[PDB]
Each structure stands twice: as C-alpha cells, then as structure tokens.
Length: 108
Length: 106
Length: 107
Length: 108
Ligand SMILES: O=P(O)(O)O[C@H]1[C@H](O)[C@@H](O)[C@H](O)[C@H](O)[C@@H]1O
Ligand SMILES: O=P(O)(O)O[C@H]1[C@H](O)[C@@H](O)[C@H](O)[C@H](O)[C@@H]1O
Ligand SMILES: O=P(O)(O)O[C@H]1[C@H](O)[C@@H](O)[C@H](O)[C@H](O)[C@@H]1O
Image 1: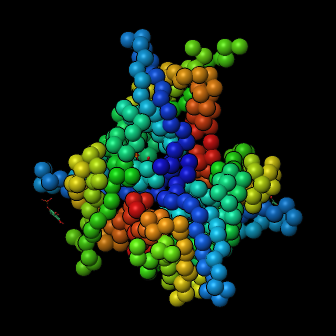
Image 2: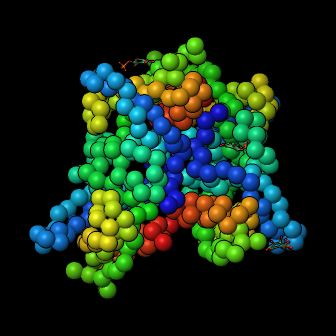
Image 3: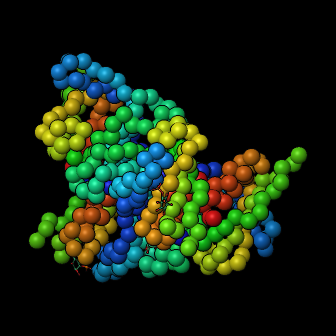
C-alpha cells in the first residue's frame, strides 16, 4: 500500500458549532490534506474529507508557551466556506510547527 | 504544486441501471478522484476518491473499444470483489488510463 | 511535476557585473536552474538552491529594470553564508510572482 | 527546514565501474530522487545528484529470502545514460519494497 505521503499523524480540529475538538488521522499529500477516521493505512482508505491545498492557506499559529494550534484558511468555497477558518491542534508546539511549515510550502 | 498522472472525462457504467454517467477524473499516485467538472479552481471536493492500493485493473477492450474494468480487492467505495466499468473516448485514450492504472495497482 | 513557478531568469554576477540567463523551476524545496525549458530532455539541474537556507530580502519598486530581487544565503551551500544573489525577471509583475512565492517559502 | 519528502533513508548504490557499493542519504520527492552525502537535513542541502523521476522507472527487485535490491532504469540521457540501469540496496527486503513501491507510483 504505497502512498505519496508528505506527513501523517493525528490532529484535533475544533468545531465552531460542536464547541469541541474532533480527532482524526490526517495525511498530507502534494494535493490534499486528507482526514481519515483511523490510522489503518491498509484498510481505512475512504477519506472523511479531502481539503484541496490549492485553495487553502495557513495563517496563524500558537506562539511557544495549548501552544500547539494553527489556523487553516479557505480561499474558495469547498469543504470550508470561502474566507472561513479552521483551527487544528497538534500534540506539541514542535509537531504543530512541522504541520504548519509543511502546509505553508505547499500553499504559497 | 499539483501531482497528477492523468486527468479527463470518463463514463462509469451502473451495473444495475445499465447506463453510463459522466464525470471528470483525476488520477494521482494514490487515488482515482471523480469531480463533477474540470474546473480545478472552483470545483474542489471530489465526488469520490478511490484508493488505488485497494484496486486492480483486470480487463480492457481490444482495438465501443474504449472500456476497462476496475476491480475492488477490499471494501471501500466499491464492495470487495466487485467491479466497475469505465468508458473513455477512444481505444488510445482508454489504454493511457489502463496502462497507468496497471502500473499503479500492480 | 510538482512545481510552484517556472520561467527564465537572469542572474547577475557580482564580480563580472553581467547577467546570465537560465530556466528556473521553483518547487516547495528548491530553486532549480536548468540550461533550457525542455523538461523531457534536459533533466539535470545546473544547480539546486535549497529554500530552507535562503531568504528573499529586497525587490525593485514599480516604474510608476524594475524587475529585480535579491536572494540571501543564511547558510553555506551553493552560495556562501551571508552573501546575496540578484535575479532579474522580464517585468515588475513577473518579478513579484517570483518574489511573493519565495517570501512565503523562505519565511 | 520543511521539505516535501515522500521517503528518506540510506541506500547503497552499486557502481559498475568501482565494483563496490556507495552509501548515500536519499530523499524522494514527487519530482526527484535526490542523493546527499549525509542525513543532516538542516545543513547538507546541495544534492550530490538529482534523478528526475519523469525519465526513470523501477523494473526488477529481489525476491524475499542480499534480498534487498532493486533496479532503477533510465528512459533518457541524464545522470544515467538512456537505457542503462542502476542497482540499489536497502537494509532489508521490507525497506527495499517501501522504496520500490513508492518509486513505482511516481514513475508510471
Ligand atoms: O472549542 P473548544 O470549546 O473545545 O475550546 C478549546 C480550544 O479551541 C483550545 O485552543 C484549547 O487549548 C482548549 O482546550 C479549549 O477547551
Ligand atoms: O558489484 P559488487 O562488486 O559491489 O558486488 C556485490 C553485489 O552486486 C550484491 O548483490 C551483494 O549483496 C554484494 O555485497 C557484492 O559485494
Ligand atoms: O540534505 P540532507 O542530506 O541532510 O538530506 C535530508 C532532507 O533534505 C530531508 O527532507 C529529510 O527529512 C532528511 O532527514 C535528509 O537527511
């Protein structure tokens, strides 16, 4: 089961409506940030959602001392309404910055 | 910064309805994605994404002579063991889809 | 081919005070130079400049050549640490496309 | 120092002329298989060579039970002469197959 993954791992996404974080298993490719319900990379291969990097940017992130959050901004209507913003939370500042920087270089 | 192998329109047959429906498909190293349209800037959410690691391509038309079969090895979008039939515009176009899919799903 | 931008740029030599032209391909990781734009037959970069080791500092203001920008080396690679290479595009508008992408990539 | 890495790790490349293996640190992106002298991802960033995937294929590999080798074939003149073949050796069959399958899906 090869896969052109640039980064993978669990992230929590804040829901503005549910007022809580939903954890998923995320996989970054050159085209999409995909969410899967689980990390079973051999069997769980229908994405919950696929966010097109061509129309997303990463804007802000936590300053080191949770300090492990970043914002993904939508430039066009898709999974996210144009102009709207999703907040992600990683395990640590360092992990967050790995996600942030990898996303940044694919969304310039 | 895209990474796509092939893109274009395909018709997918319904086994039960015995009819074809058309979509815009994008083949990447990981998925066969279907979109409603070819507008990569405004049509951003795949109708479905078929994981290649769970599929094989089995047969195709000989020189419509533009069909090929995608077989599901595991449950996903397609039930395990089932088969979806796609139709391109020409034999030559179909063979481009097939030859890439064959390598990707080996 | 996963690329952000491609096109011809002229690179100035500090000491020779002249420009030389190449075909550049900007990816998330590198600014690559090739001799030509033939991506099927010209396969080996003349040089590959790692973006994580660079920053872009200044660029020309619009004339209203206004098409230059500066790439600064933060570490020793193709360019010695602390040194600067100057590139020239065909227009201010083209230059700003290069600069704006580079600014984001090298932040 | 973010980087669009699909896979990275040490490989040994056989030299037909030196009659020996040369070890390098390899990084696979969607565009190239790069070799670096070392794994210092923060400082060693001039590739020793960059092999364009658009004109390479992977042809054969070892059968399990060294059984950790694969062949990279050149379709065009570049680092390798058109029609010529380079042999790589990984640490294990499993590692080799990870390299082989990741290369295969980027070179169809
Ligand atoms: O959206 P909810 O209600 O889940 O709020 C939380 C946050 O979004 C965090 O920044 C934060 O670190 C918190 O733990 C806080 O609970
Ligand atoms: O071409 P050289 O001389 O480098 O020979 C080697 C091999 O090609 C390997 O299969 C093998 O596992 C060996 O290590 C052997 O040295
Ligand atoms: O430039 P060097 O030789 O240091 O190569 C490294 C990389 O540039 C990384 O993407 C990567 O994740 C590596 O760790 C790899 O060592």
